[PDB]
Amino acid sequence: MDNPNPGPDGEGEVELEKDSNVVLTTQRDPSTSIPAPVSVKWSRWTSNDVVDDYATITSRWYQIAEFVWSKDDPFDKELARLILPRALLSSIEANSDAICDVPNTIPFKVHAYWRGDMEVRVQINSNKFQVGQLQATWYYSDHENLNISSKRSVYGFSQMDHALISASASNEAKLVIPFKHVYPFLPTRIVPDWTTGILDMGALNIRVIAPLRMSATGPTTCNVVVFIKLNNSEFTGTSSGKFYASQIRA
Amino acid sequence: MDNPNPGPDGEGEVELEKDSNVVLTTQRDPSTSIPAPVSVKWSRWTSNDVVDDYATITSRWYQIAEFVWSKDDPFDKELARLILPRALLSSIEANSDAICDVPNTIPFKVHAYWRGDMEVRVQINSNKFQVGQLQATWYYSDHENLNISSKRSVYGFSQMDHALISASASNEAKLVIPFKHVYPFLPTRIVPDWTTGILDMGALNIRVIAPLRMSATGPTTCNVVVFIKLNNSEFTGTSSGKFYASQIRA
Amino acid sequence: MDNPNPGPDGEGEVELEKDSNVVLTTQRDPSTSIPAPVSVKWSRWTSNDVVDDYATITSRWYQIAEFVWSKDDPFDKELARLILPRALLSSIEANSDAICDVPNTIPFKVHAYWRGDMEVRVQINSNKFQVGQLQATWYYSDHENLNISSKRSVYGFSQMDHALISASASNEAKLVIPFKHVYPFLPTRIVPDWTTGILDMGALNIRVIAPLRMSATGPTTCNVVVFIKLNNSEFTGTSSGKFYASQIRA
Amino acid sequence: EESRNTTVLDTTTTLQSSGFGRAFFGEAFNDLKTLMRRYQLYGQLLLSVTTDKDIDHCMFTFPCLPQGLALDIGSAGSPHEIFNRCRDGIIPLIASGYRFYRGDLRYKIVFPSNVNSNIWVQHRPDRRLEGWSAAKIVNCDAVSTGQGVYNHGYASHIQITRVNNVIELEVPFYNATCYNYLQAFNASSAASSYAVSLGEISVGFQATSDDIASIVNKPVTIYYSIGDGMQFSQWVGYQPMMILDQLPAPVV
Amino acid sequence: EESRNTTVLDTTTTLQSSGFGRAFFGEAFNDLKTLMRRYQLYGQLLLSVTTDKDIDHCMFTFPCLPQGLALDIGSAGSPHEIFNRCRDGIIPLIASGYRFYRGDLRYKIVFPSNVNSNIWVQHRPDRRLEGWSAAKIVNCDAVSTGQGVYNHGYASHIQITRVNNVIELEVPFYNATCYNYLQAFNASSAASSYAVSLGEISVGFQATSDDIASIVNKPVTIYYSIGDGMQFSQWVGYQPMMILDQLPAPVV
Amino acid sequence: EESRNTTVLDTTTTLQSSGFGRAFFGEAFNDLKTLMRRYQLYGQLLLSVTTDKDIDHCMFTFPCLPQGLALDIGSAGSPHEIFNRCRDGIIPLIASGYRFYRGDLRYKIVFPSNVNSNIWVQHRPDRRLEGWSAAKIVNCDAVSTGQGVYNHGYASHIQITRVNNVIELEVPFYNATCYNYLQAFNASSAASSYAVSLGEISVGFQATSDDIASIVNKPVTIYYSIGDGMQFSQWVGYQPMMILDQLPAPVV
């Protein structure tokens, strides 16, 4: 035990996570937090249309958020309230191009309804000498609640299960989010019985539990990048792409 | 081998040392040094009174010394000459309260004679970037020797067995001290054939072998805390507490 | 896994490499690079004289190069073009004394021809916070080539096999060089059919791939020391020591 | 991670488990589903007749949900002292800590005893709940739609007040959802409002306008429990609480 | 280390191996020894008679080595357009990447067809190669030593130009070395020069000075391959290359 | 730790063990207990009679301990040249490196040969040793207590000087301790002084005051070894030593 021998290759073991044609590596073990067991398929109950998961394209990773986490951010501080089935699309529309330009999200342009799980990796690139800690918490249906504006603090999301991203360890936060909405499908576009709040399963929100702490000449900033996989999906209701409207900018 | 993956929980394994109701933890492996094999009980030879070890209270740990070890302390420098069966009592009387106020030392207030082993943990809280080294050495019956005033240096206590407390490793010094006095019991109070030098088995003394070394903006101080357990004890000669007098202040 | 417990003895495991009466230790695993398989003995074909390897003296390690590698050295920078059967002798003559003064090289003074392998350890003593990388490359018969003056760069020696000495890991470069010359023996002195270019098997040359990088108050220099063993040797043609002339200074 | 546990520095010995009071009190309190089946006061209202009511006209309505109603403290002069002083009770204090529910509810509406008139009770699962505003007991005004009257096909029951003035119900889970929302509800989606309350119970008297005067300003108290099929699903932590004994006393 | 491979971040699936063109073209190209046995143009020269040549006098010589000759672009007025434009060919492009060689060579010298005279060819393994300067085809001047004439004991062959004007050779490894040098050669050691070329082939015509006029300024082209025993030993990386299609075009 | 051994960087081969001189000299020197049993000079004194001595009066006394006496160099004019020049000998050089002892001692007192008188020797284990001051040979003055005379019950022996002027002893471990102190002794505790010396041997002549004149200023030398039961217990490192051949020579 405890025999450090670094070389030109480096010291530690690098773990992978391969998808279709996306491999993204982390030195550190993830702090996984799984808020619910894995969802059943549920196309038998409400779909006669041809249903197929496009796992060769949809299960790839895609960056949907990157943000500087400075030490100027105080203690109780939001960093990103990502609405994850929306944020996969609104990140692309924030890149000033359409949904059909990205391989991950072309069945959202075509199909009408979606049910699937979501993997989320909230990777950080902090220094070893920086001291601080994030938490990444998934809340099911944030915008269908009106007192969440008072719950949205680090004391309230520490009670439900969540991941912790310490800035010392440069930790990575795996986050397996299965589908639990009230209705067993999320429409990707304006559907006859609801138009407002489209494709909103809930909110990944990333508060600060400890701010960044350092010396006077220490590295101030800290970049955080969020990736999302859409693994156990299924799309139903093949429809035209001209009925898909752009997401709300938020 | 050599796969560093820290998390929010930290990296390494934490070892414990539980006693009655005192658990004190160290990240590092101890540098144990045992000057003698474990003593036999020896109440058969000199006691008809009811003898009982109070292991639910006496075998707890108790802090008896804490001292700042600065870089201003030179090379051959005493830091603490603790007389350990006395220093357990004189630390309490240095806290400006009586011996009967502490659970560890109430049988010293009652009983007249004591024989037992002593565990000593000399814990340090140095930084990883500090460089220096203590030694913790137990000398049997310091004050029954008159040339110890010339022996008391780091060259003389390196010859007998001793522990080393490096300031880089933040090392901990376990030190198992069994009972070897000339007489098989140490009186806790003024006893008819000796009055001076009461409850003096010997001296733990903590010299400096390397002083603290650092940069100009490095952490100057270094706190050292000494704990003592009184494990294989036995007390005999139940007597009044009004014959117990306070220890010499030293 | 990953349980750091340093002590007074230090943390890691130290590996050895013992020879006749020379033990030299490295904390780090070597980056071995072996340009050819191990050579056969070949005294049967061209020697009737008494042939003996002096493995109790010749197989010791001997320092033949030490050089400061500062950050002032640019990217494509030679640090040492060592001609290794010569550099073992020219280092000694650079120490302003004869070849017969060193135990490793007395059979070069006596014998006329030599065939053997050479171990080379290019040890570095960089800090953990320094960033940079050497390569140690063996080229067979540098001076029998005229376009090597254009090959001598880090892009050309990266193509053949070579060792890498990263300044972060303080890496060590083992380098097993078997005998491959055109003729199966290298003369140690002026021999009837060639006088120029004596005892030249080739060149160990140590370029820079990444220069040293550090802070403003970081450690600027970096010392590199090269050791050589002469293990599977054999010497033939016992001759007088007065026919051995001194090597060219270079 | 949330419930990770790195280094348990335990000084304790073994404590004898009582079985959540089974050893002392003869009953276990571990299962919090069976504490939820103790009846809690759901609502409390005075019967206020506005216009001339026919026999069909519903006296009051309320959306039926385990989250508790939009809490009526009362008017600033006359507060309902239980929902003023004893804030929120138990079932929305436990349902405050969850996100979805799938199950039934029980009601046990208690009527005044001065009235004698026969009372009908409709369950209407058609009704959507348009926001947490007006998620409360509605004293009904003059009839404009089919909301304000007795209707045919919906499941009803008629308590005879002369025999016993309490009707006890079991309101089933008639939603087209997997499960319904359980926190307070702002109605973002237009079909999300079909998924909060189990339905919308309307209680109405069969009295004419001459017997309607004995009904006026009599109390009707409603209770509820969760009825053995209720399964609160997703753990969501609690919100900021308010401590009750720090509420100010009515200084003389 | 060189060929170490720390973390292969592979996004690829499996690609079907063709067997280096065996699946498509009916032939494998993995072994680069058998591509080296395709004949490459070694040299190219015009027969320039200087003095009155006897029957013994060698018309030209060349040191025989797989490294390619010291590359003759030509005079600045009239360049040899292949070695000007198509630099260096294949066999010294592969032998540029190695250090030692041990093996034989083949030559296939092609003679002009206007000449008829009988042609002798000597292999002379005695000859040392004094540096990369004059490691080239030498049109021989007047005879001063035994270099310039037909000699007795060396292995020779006589092609009759009237039957076929091409002599095909197999020049054996007659060195006292383990293996010979393969890069360009600066001749540091005096005996190292015995270890570059396999020997020194001299081609000479048996014509008198009246038939020597039809020989003048006729081309003789030489080829070479590596002849099945050639084993390039020590891997040495390539030197700086020059890209050919960036060479300037002859602007009109 | 003290005797830890992290990385033995051994360049040595195997050295043939002699067995601590057993292979060469026919005897092993590993056990240092048997070197301690060679007799060392303990004390050295001139018989100085002060007052008129009776037959009972002890001529001199000394506390009996393996630590060596409080070392008498002598007066500044006439030093005892062995304890001046040859400092401390072997047995307190080994007993300097230990803390406790439990065992016996041997003495072999050598008397002058000019005297003839019969000599008695008392062992007195009652006697406490009051500090390292006066842990030495005491020429006894006039009698005030029972210290100064022959006593009854204590173990005695009478050497006849006419037969052999050396009495050889074995002073047993008669202490009530586990083991006694072995370094120099400052007498902190009042009962600690019962635990340094084995007892207190007093040697006395049976001569009257007419034969007392031949006794005056004759040397009596004492020896000691450790007598086969001596077990030095706790390892304590050595103190600062003084090197003997750096002591100054008596310059003429």
Image (spheres, coloured by chain):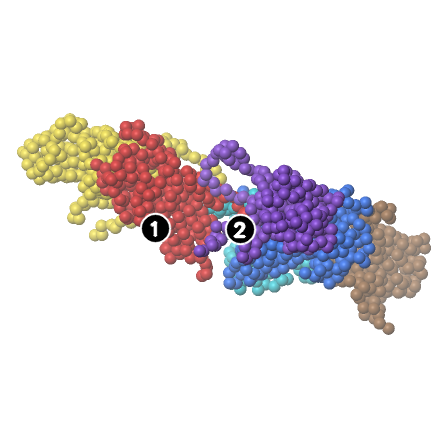
Chain colours: A cyan, B blue, C red, D brown, E yellow, F purple
> Which residue appears at 41% of the width and 55% of the height?
C221
Is residue C20 in sight in this rendering? yes
Amino acid on which disc 1 is placed: Glu
Q: Which numbered disc covers residue F81?
A: 2
Dividing the picture into quadrants, the one containing residue B246 is bottom right
Amino acid on which disc 2 is placed: Glu
Residue sitting nearer the eye, E203 or B249: B249
As displayed, is residue B240 above or below residue E152? below
Q: Position of residue B198 (x, y in %)?
A: 72, 55
Mark 2 element type = helix
As displayed, is residue D216 above or below residue E190? below
As displayed, is residue C132 above or below residue E119? below
Q: Which numbered disc covers residue C78?
A: 1
**Left or right: D128, with D225 as reference point:** left
Is residue E7 in sight in this rendering? no
Residue sitting nearer the eye, A228 or D5: D5
Q: Residues within 10 Å of mark 2 (few under 14, many from 20)?
A: few
Q: Position of residue D193 (x, y in %)?
A: 71, 56
